[PDB]
């Protein structure tokens, strides 16, 4: 039998990560026919947020691509990516990722058995709730789901909101049932998971980045013969490039599809409104500056300019 390579993730198929994973499957099976096959498991059908990294290290799955927010059990260094309003836009994110500090972060978990293979984009996060979030005061007392990140919890603490860490697979139902008031996510996730059907208002805040690290286990990666590993790595690189293109396309397409539905009201921030949000969030950077490194924050800030 060909060696089966399993790739699990938590998103819908028709998304940047969903498409990256399928492109990787296509390229491996084209270039190494009969030698390797890639099985892709979207929508948390095999492993979900809470168990995927444990599964990876057990070699129950060979590739995963978690949000950069979801690595705190293995390193505190990736917390930089969660800081609110650190990056102006995806161009700045990419520059930071491709610079020396960003490249070094790919190896931040290597002694824990996790090999960083590349960064894959999704997009900037927007707030949703059942009220406009024009100013920080509008979030006070509201319950927001967050990815399992202390930085993201602190982001909501900073405005007197109540953060709740929950796996991605639960978010739609939590919103639907009003167990939570709101959440934060990209247009692509908001559209593909139908969050906009159970939230009356989406505020275009662009207040943080949701990106991924594509990872494998050291044990699996070392178990490959070097020539086959090189072919697999090149296929992965090409799949990430395609996924990044899709990410940018979906960010525009899916915003428009949400607007077309007329089910959720878009809320835009004035410059002064945005600045109020920026200012109230800066203390989150101060809370984490030691763990993350002042030097690393400064490298990220400089990537904007
Ligand atoms: Cl885990
Ligand atoms: Cl929590």
Image (tube, rainbow, N blue to C red):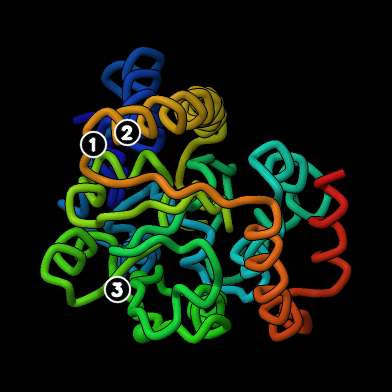
273 vs 11: above or below: below
288 vs 217: above or below: below
Crowding near the residue tagged with mark 3, few <14, some 14–19, many ≥20 C-alpha atoms within 10 Å: some
Please indicate whether residue 108 sits to the left or right of residue 6 in the image: right
Label whose residue precedes the other's in the sequence (1 or 3): 3
For label 3, the residue is: 166
Please indicate whether residue 29 sits to the left or right of residue 154 in the image: left
Residue at x-position 22% and y-position 33%: 261
Crowding near the residue tagged with mark 1, few <14, some 14–19, many ≥20 C-alpha atoms within 10 Å: few
Q: Position of residue 30 (x, y in %)?
A: 35, 13
Q: Is the CB of mark 1 within 8 Å of ligand 2? A: no
Residue at x-position 76% and y-position 82%: 286
Label whose residue precedes the other's in the sequence (2 or 3): 3
SS at circle 2: helix
For label 1, the residue is: 262
For label 2, the residue is: 259
- Circles 1 and 2 in contact, beta carbons < 8 Å: yes
20 vs 297: above or below: above
Please indicate whether residue 68 sits to the left or right of residue 58 in the image: right
Residue at x-position 70% and y-position 36%: 91
**Does residue 258 show up?**
yes
- Check the image and name the residue furthest to the top: 30
């Amino acid at each position: 039998a060909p060696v089966e390579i399993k790739f699990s993730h938590v998103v819908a198929e028709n998304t940047p990560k969903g498409q990256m994973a399928l492109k990787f499957k296509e390229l491996v099976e084209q270039r190494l026919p009969g030698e390797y096959t890639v099985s892709v498991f979207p929508n948390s059908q095999l492993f979900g947020d809470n168990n995927e990294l444990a599964a990876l290290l057990l070699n129950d799955v060979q590739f995963v691509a978690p949000s950069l927010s979801k690595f705190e059990r293995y390193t505190k260094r990736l917390q930089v990516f969660d800081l609110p309003f650190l990056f102006n836009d995806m161009d700045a994110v990419n520059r930071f990722q491709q610079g020396e500090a960003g490249q070094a972060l790919l190896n931040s978990m290597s002694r824990k058995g996790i090999v960083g293979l590349g960064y894959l984009h999704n997009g900037m996060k927007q707030f949703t709730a059942n009220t406009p979030l024009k100013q920080p005061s509008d979030a006070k007392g509201l319950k927001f789901r967050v990815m399992a990140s202390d930085v993201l919890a602190a982001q909501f603490d900073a405005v007197g909101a109540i953060p709740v860490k929950k796996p991605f697979s639960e978010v739609f139902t939590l919103l639907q049932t009003r167990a939570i008031d709101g959440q934060e996510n990209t247009w692509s996730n908001t559209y593909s998971q139908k969050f906009y059907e159970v939230q009356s208002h989406i505020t275009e805040s662009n207040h943080g980045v949701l990106d991924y690290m594509v990872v494998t286990s050291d044990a699996f990666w070392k178990s490959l013969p070097a020539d086959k590993r090189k072919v697999i790595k090149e296929a992965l690189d090409e799949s990430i490039a395609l996924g990044n293109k899709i990410a940018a396309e979906k960010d525009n397409e899916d915003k428009q599809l949400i607007l077309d539905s007329k089910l959720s009201q878009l809320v835009t921030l004035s410059p002064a409104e945005r600045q109020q949000w920026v200012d109230v969030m800066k203390p989150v950077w101060s809370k984490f500056e030691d763990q993350v490194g002042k030097d690393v924050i400064e490298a990220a800030v400089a990537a904007n300019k």
